[PDB]
Image 1 (cartoon, rainbow, N blue to C red):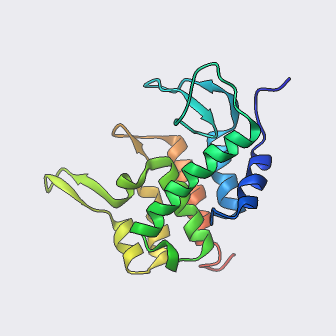
Image 2 (cartoon, rainbow, N blue to C red; image 1 turned 180 degrees about the vertical axis):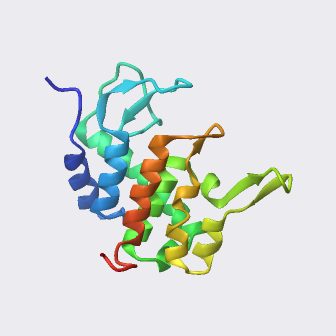
Length: 178
């Protein structure tokens, strides 16, 4: 049967369009985290989801094109890429770091990468990952990806795993591959 769609096929379309910078490894990382579904489904705190983690333009029971789901994915990727470019010096970092960062922003949203609420200081303050990004210190930046593993103030095994996959990507080509 068929309800699950192919990430690999979505990757070739998005890469073919020539808009997204994030590389194959980044699209693979993002795609496998989310999975790919033509049928809209319900996540906790239920709001409908499409394709590859898409929640915009989603109508229950409405099955999307293969190309429409790539279109959707592209759009969400470019939002995440804008975050990295506008706020983390994306234009200056290499592709692997950029792609890992994009994956983080796709998942957590830009706001959560830029600042966090300091209970000590009683206000939101700049993150270390942003500090290191602005300094062009990519290795240090990458190595802060594991800071972002909480949901509703609780760490998730899945987010630990994800942030570590992102960190490994971020750093390839930046450190001894062995």
